[PDB]
Image (tube, coloured by chain):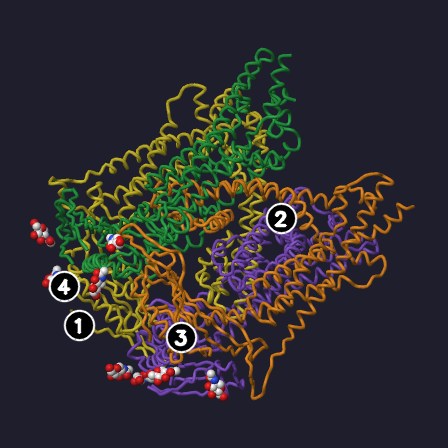
Chain colours: A orange, B green, C yellow, D purple
Amino acid sequence: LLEDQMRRKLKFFFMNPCEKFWARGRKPWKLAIQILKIAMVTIQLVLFGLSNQMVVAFKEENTIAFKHLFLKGYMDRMDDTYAVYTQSDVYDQLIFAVNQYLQLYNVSVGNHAYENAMAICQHFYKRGNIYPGNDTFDIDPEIETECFFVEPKLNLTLDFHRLLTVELQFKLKAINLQTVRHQELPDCYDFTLTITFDNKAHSGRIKISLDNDISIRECKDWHVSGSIQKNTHYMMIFDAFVILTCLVSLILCIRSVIRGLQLQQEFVNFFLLHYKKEVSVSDQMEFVNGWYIMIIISDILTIIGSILKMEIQAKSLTSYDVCSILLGTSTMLVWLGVIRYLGFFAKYNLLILTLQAALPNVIRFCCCAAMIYLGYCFCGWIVLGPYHDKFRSLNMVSECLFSLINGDDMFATFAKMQQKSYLVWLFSRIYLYSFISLFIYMILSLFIALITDTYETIKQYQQDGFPETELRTFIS
Amino acid sequence: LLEDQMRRKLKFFFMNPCEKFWARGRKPWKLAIQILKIAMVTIQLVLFGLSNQMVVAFKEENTIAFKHLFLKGYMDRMDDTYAVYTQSDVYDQLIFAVNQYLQLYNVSVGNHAYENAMAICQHFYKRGNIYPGNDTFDIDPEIETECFFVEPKLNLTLDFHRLLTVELQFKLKAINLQTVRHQELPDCYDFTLTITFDNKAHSGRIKISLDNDISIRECKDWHVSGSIQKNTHYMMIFDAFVILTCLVSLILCIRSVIRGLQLQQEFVNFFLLHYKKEVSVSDQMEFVNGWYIMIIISDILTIIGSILKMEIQAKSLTSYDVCSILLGTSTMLVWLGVIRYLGFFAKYNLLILTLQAALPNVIRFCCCAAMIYLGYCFCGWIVLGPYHDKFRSLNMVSECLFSLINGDDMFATFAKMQQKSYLVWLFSRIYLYSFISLFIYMILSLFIALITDTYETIKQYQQDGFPETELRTFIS
Amino acid sequence: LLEDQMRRKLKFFFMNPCEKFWARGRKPWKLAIQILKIAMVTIQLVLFGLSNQMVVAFKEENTIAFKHLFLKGYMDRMDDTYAVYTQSDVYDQLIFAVNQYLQLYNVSVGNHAYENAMAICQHFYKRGNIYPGNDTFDIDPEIETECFFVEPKLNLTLDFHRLLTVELQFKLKAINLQTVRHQELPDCYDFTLTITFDNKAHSGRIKISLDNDISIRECKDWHVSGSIQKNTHYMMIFDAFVILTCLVSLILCIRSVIRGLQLQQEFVNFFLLHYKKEVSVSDQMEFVNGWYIMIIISDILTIIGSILKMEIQAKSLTSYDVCSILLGTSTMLVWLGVIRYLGFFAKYNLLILTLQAALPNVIRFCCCAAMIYLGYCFCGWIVLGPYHDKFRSLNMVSECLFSLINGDDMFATFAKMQQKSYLVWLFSRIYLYSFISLFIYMILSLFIALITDTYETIKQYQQDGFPETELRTFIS
Amino acid sequence: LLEDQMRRKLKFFFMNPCEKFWARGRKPWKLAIQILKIAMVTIQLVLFGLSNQMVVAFKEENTIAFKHLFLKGYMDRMDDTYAVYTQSDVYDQLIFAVNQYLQLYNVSVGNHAYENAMAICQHFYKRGNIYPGNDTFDIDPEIETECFFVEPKLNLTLDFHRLLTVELQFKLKAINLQTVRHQELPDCYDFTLTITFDNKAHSGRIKISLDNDISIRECKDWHVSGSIQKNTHYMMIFDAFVILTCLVSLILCIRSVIRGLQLQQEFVNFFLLHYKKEVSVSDQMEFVNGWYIMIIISDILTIIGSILKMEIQAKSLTSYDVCSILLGTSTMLVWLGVIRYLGFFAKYNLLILTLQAALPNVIRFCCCAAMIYLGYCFCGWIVLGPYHDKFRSLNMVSECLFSLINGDDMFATFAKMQQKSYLVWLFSRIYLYSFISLFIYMILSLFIALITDTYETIKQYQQDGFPETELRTFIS
Ligand SMILES: *[C@@H]1O[C@H](CO)[C@@H](O)[C@H](O)[C@H]1NC(C)=O
Ligand SMILES: *[C@@H]1O[C@H](CO)[C@@H](O)[C@H](O)[C@H]1NC(C)=O
Ligand SMILES: *[C@@H]1O[C@H](CO)[C@@H](O)[C@H](O)[C@H]1NC(C)=O
Ligand SMILES: *[C@@H]1O[C@H](CO)[C@@H](O)[C@H](O)[C@H]1NC(C)=O
Ligand SMILES: *[C@@H]1O[C@H](CO)[C@@H](O)[C@H](O)[C@H]1NC(C)=O
Ligand SMILES: *[C@@H]1O[C@H](CO)[C@@H](O)[C@H](O)[C@H]1NC(C)=O
Ligand SMILES: *[C@@H]1O[C@H](CO)[C@@H](O)[C@H](O)[C@H]1NC(C)=O
Ligand SMILES: *[C@@H]1O[C@H](CO)[C@@H](O)[C@H](O)[C@H]1NC(C)=O
């Protein structure tokens, strides 16, 4: 009958292993292109990560060597957050830094060379008038930058209370030999340096640092072993081929989505002429694969990630952030997607059967426990903020109470109180003993017991059929 | 009948979602004022926390800049607990500190200025006579403070064995620009400084520190951008409106408490004329809402917290401790109170059904395990106190054995023993191996198994009715 | 009958709450003396701990002040394990230390004074002959100490390869004011100092340290506030009273032990004339209380602990180690013993019902898992000993694998490898990934599941009687 | 019948306690040689570990003393990874190191003496031409080492951009007295030193270190206490005896393997003539003991380990790595093997019954969760690599996410972000909050619930027989 026709095509709509569906009758390979996609996407991501990692290593080493070249009294391994608290000391610092830049060729071991320029920016208030003795001040809140230019020993005067910030900016060129000679990547390193003196807090605490922005290019004229060389970028082609595969498994699985859609309304509309039932929810959910949706999303993300890696390599800005985040989140979703093809073996379906059956319940529970958490987190923030080093911004408080839910860095917290206000110090102890002894044992063990319970129920589903659907009664 | 009348009003006394009670017949909004309360109380607490946080940031920066201005050989990032062990060194220190205060205008970068005064307090024993060679001493235990006053290089003599303490006290005024210009808060900073030399232990170990007390005020005459300004405090009004809302949800829920009270004796006294049973416990407990009690408590605490924030802002002492603790504990209870309105959805009641059904049992268990804990904690204190850095005061021992219950900072503990007394060193290892291997696995896993078990029982309550009460038999 | 007579006295042999036994007919108080014992023993232990703690605090402060007085280039907070690697440096060190001792009165802030003496011990080999160039050495392994005595600048010659060790020994007297004036404790502090130079390893690494031995006495002639004083030790009397109470609850509970014994053979021998069964095990176990045994043991330990605290206070050696360990382990057992009297309430018996029913099974399991642990611990020791900072002695390896069972200091371990030998470095990672991923999840979760299971079974015992004993069938 | 004959010999093939098999009729001892093996193998491994440990202690002390003798400005306890950033500083360093080697006899405390030689290796590029100003470079990538030899103050010129590395190599002989005099081990210590200056990264960051290779020998002419001595190595004989025992328990258990094999085909082939069933899997698995296999493997490994310890001691290279790994993994397997003889008691079989019944399921589960883990680990690597100190190489990322699964070093991770790129900084927080809150609670609690469940099933196996095998139906 009509019934048996439509249900008969349906029976092989749903054959879960594509091995099992093809087992009916022969179809040319699709799944092979998805395995190819995995191998591609991850080979791209690895080949990317290694290169980027070498460039980062070089920027790290160089910015360290700079920290010791241009910061007076940087301890020859490392010091950090170094600040100068007397105005004679700020003057001595400035004089030193500039004198190092001008004497850089005698001083430095590195191949650092100038570009063919030291910009001294001084940002002070338009009309600064401050008299803490009178307990009165008068200001116009503009910023006027009186600048300098130094060429490869000056005179300067800085009225300090007027002074908002200072800066030193000089370009330096470095050539990286190992990376260029061994492999083909751009090996010219332009370095912009900014030595900034934050007076913004106006605490009398002059804060110094050294910022490094590294813009890559290629050496125009380049000779290896007496010959000449030009870097051939094959990864340029490789990105392309990965966009191709990813596009194909975009399309094929889009058709796999919409075909099933039209079979879903085909099914439900069929169902009225005969049995006249609905399940607008159950078997619309059923036909949507939901793993195909993931393949499509990680596909889109891999396309845009690859394109951005391609422009970012060609035009060669090398900021890399928004490209890395995409091309990473994609491979995360792809490798996640491999679980289905583990599942075709059928000895592993439990993690994504119960992880899907656990979520509808946990989400409810999680919400209700999140109310407690917030109400806890605020009070921790304010009451503990003046004193405890960890509770300062609201977020850090979130990483404390999340660290402590998981029982990590505990005794640190009890011992980092300042003890200065006995009342508050004691409060913190009621706070932490409370939170730990509630949100670990009670709430956590309730949550974990919830998931394990769900695992029991899905276990005996795996043992005795499943919840019976009109579909799976009707396909059988 | 009479029965059906009283029970009939009762049926809608208990309609749990106020949505569900109003579902009967229309009532004007109350619950809306409770949601308004939440939004208020937390907006107050956040707007408070941010301001207080900025004031703390400024005090931190400044007291650091002071630590480096007035303490000889403070390493230009930080050193801590710095102490001077030769009397020549104490003299050099004092001379330095005073000389910095008098030269402060040449030295400092900050806008620190004097107030229109250096108080040198020297606290020595009345009749000090000490002769450790004779193994004999004679003292009269009074304290006589021979003081100084310095005005913007002295002669001083300190007999050291007589000397109990020393101090230097000088006011310094600092103006904070960023906070005043960007937002309206008091921006005058009075600083009292106390440089204290503890000889109290008389170990030959002279301990130094720098204490900072910051009293806020407002700049009398103040001009921004060529104009004049006066800070308008709207948060003054905001505190008021929050006291109002909080008072209203105090009153309305008090009536909600007592109304149910008179219905509880109305119910139980009714019950004698007919069925002649009691449940003096069960359904007196039932009528008291217990969530209304919380709303009332967090309400009181929010009232007093707000008033204290208001006086503390107006009169402007700015100690802030007892205000912060209240206004925090309140918002903690309020956000906790949100769980009920999550519960009206009815997919979340499990956490506060089982968290209430778990407490009567756990409390018993907890008590019995607390006996073990104390008996463990004392022996740890004394036997381990001379040697292990962590076990010193009794409390710290409490935070060790609580840290170790939760398995945090373990190898630290085994490695911090002093090994000097082999017998005791070995004892500590029997101690810790024992405690960990008992109080984690055995007692903890028993406790967690208790709560999870309770969760099972309340789960199948959620599945099949509840324990049957004469009330809920009688309302049905 | 005879049966009913003996069983009739037995029925009140076993009345578990002594409240419940006295409920029969009146008996004078015993249990009151046990509560008195608890209050005593712990008040003794606390009053002890505080005093000892103050003496430790003073020794700590003083030995620090010494470390900075007599060790050249001790950084004015702390340095640790400081060693001198050139012979010119050792000479300069020695000269400095001695010069400080002789100039101590100008130098020190403290009240340290000599006793009415600097002993320079030099331990060198009898016949030292060493020639690492010839790859040949000749020695006679004796120790001959050529000593000195210095009186308040020398000439010295040390042949270094012959030199085994050096030492400086000088007594210094310190008077502690706060403790004597505020409370009555001995306040004379004799200090023996030993500055030792370990050359024993003969690595060219000369290791220095400062050892402190503090012998207490009382100031002979002592005047407070113009009057005279002698410290009255009431704690001397207090120790006595505690020995008394402890002795009484020794005796009374010994009789409680042997009475039940003679009722146990009385019972079992009775049982042959009639029913002719044995339970040589079950109801010999039953009559022995097992809590009385604890009271007796903690009693003995409290007696000896108190006596040793009394001699150690009177004769006043003040080593304190073997006294502290006893008097601590006792109070640990006593406070543990309080659980029974919590149990008389009868809402708490579960922890010591199931903790006793869990032990016979766990002990078996524990043994079998200990085999795995040892076999793991050895291989960790040897294979990882040359490289990983943590695995060195066998014991430390035991505290690593115990730290890691409990999941504490993990990333530290993976990051502390030396990476020098790639093969071994990789081995350590198979080692740790293996051990963690076996001995946590598998073995630990098996153990914890064992205890929780036992808790289930004892729960439904608490619900439906118990295992039925011929006794408890026969007393009923 | 034939059936009863073969099954009758079989009944005592399988008697699990060899005590229980011998209980039939007397057999001479085998198991005694296995207990002897355990005692041997571990006594060898301990006696080895101690010796090796003393040699390591001496190398550690000496290489430290060297770090302070030859590295300018090594802080007299320790500094680490010390690097020199100006070419004047590199020159001063070199001059210092060499001057220390030549003056070593005045300088050092140790008995270090030369061997009867300072090799200065300088590795520079063949044709170095570098011009970072032109953004052009030309190189021929060879390495040409222009060397020196110094004999107990030079002139040197190093063109720095050409310079790849530098080195200083000098032998030093040290005699260790304590080890030779107290026990018989080789006590001559040859030290090769390499002071290496890595310029390889060409960051301007010249990295220095001190490498130590220690080759042991024996002192040719050696006299103790006026007499003469030659070290008698009895451990040479001891290794032999252990190889013997290990070989015997190799052979005997090989026969125990193959005998059971021929009884397995004897059994299955027998089974066709009568009942005609197979179980090619079940009872081929059954006859293979699987514990004998372990004894054989740990036996092989102990043989090769012992032989390598013997050659490595005689020829005396003392690299020790591949010997230690073997001789360790063996004793790990042996002590593991002890569990069976614990099992003969029969109160402990549960751990290796359920640990074997848990593995077939977990392995499936573990695989599927490993897919998630990898896909997570890559994205963590790349997206977090530029910034987070922990995520750098892929492996370290593996030890982060394994550290965090187990909840160790958490707050460290949230606080080690660089915050420089707000987008990425926020990403890391979605990353970590996600991973922790999925891979701990959900996946971990699922895994642990799996093992505990398996423990339940094997528990009630222990209670009611086992899965019934035609064998154990047929032997009965
Ligand atoms: C380095 O200093 C010398 C003088 O000491 C000078 O002759 C030389 O030009 C300086 N280096 C450079 C690159 O100018
Ligand atoms: C107050 O302001 C006036 C400028 O009108 C200035 O001359 C005077 O010095 C100020 N007072 C102090 C204490 O600095
Ligand atoms: C700073 O020192 C100079 C002398 O070097 C003196 O003239 C000046 O008055 C000092 N500063 C102040 C604020 O007095
Ligand atoms: C003992 O006290 C007397 C004062 O009566 C003093 O002169 C003498 O120096 C003291 N002894 C010592 C050793 O200081
Ligand atoms: C301290 O040194 C001075 C000389 O500078 C000397 O007169 C005095 O006696 C010394 N102190 C003591 C206690 O001898
Ligand atoms: C070897 O020993 C002799 C003493 O007999 C000594 O003179 C000679 O210097 C030694 N050799 C070396 C290299 O020190
Ligand atoms: C140590 O230096 C002195 C000169 O101060 C010299 O005579 C002696 O020979 C040096 N040591 C050695 C072992 O040469
Ligand atoms: C470019 O290279 C030439 C060598 O042909 C050299 O003379 C010139 O100085 C280089 N330019 C710079 C800026 O160093």
Label 2, label 3: how many angstroms apart (C-alpha)? 54 Å
Where is residue B273? Give x, y as percent: 58, 10
Distance from Cα at disc 1 to Cα at disc 2? 76 Å
Q: Nearer the viewer, residue A275 or C381?
A: A275
Q: Amino acid at mark 3?
A: Tyr
Above or below: residue A77 compared with residue D168: above
Pointer 1 with pointer 3, Cβ within 8 A: no
Which of the chains bears the disc numbered 4?
C
Q: Amino acid at mark 1?
A: Asn
Estimate how packed mark 4 is, as few (under 14), some (14 to 19) or many (20 or more) residues with alpha carbons within 10 Å: few
Circle 3: is it few (<14), some (14-19), or many (20+) Cα within 10 Å?
many
The kind of secondary structure element at disc 3 is loop
Q: Are marks 3 and 4 on the same chain?
A: no
Which quadrant does the C terminus of chain C fall into? top right
| Position above or below: D259 against B336 | below
Q: Residues within 10 Å of mark 2 (few under 14, many from 20)?
A: many
Check chain identity for marks 2 and 4: say if they share one.
Answer: no
Which one is closest to the eye, mark 1 or mark 2? 2
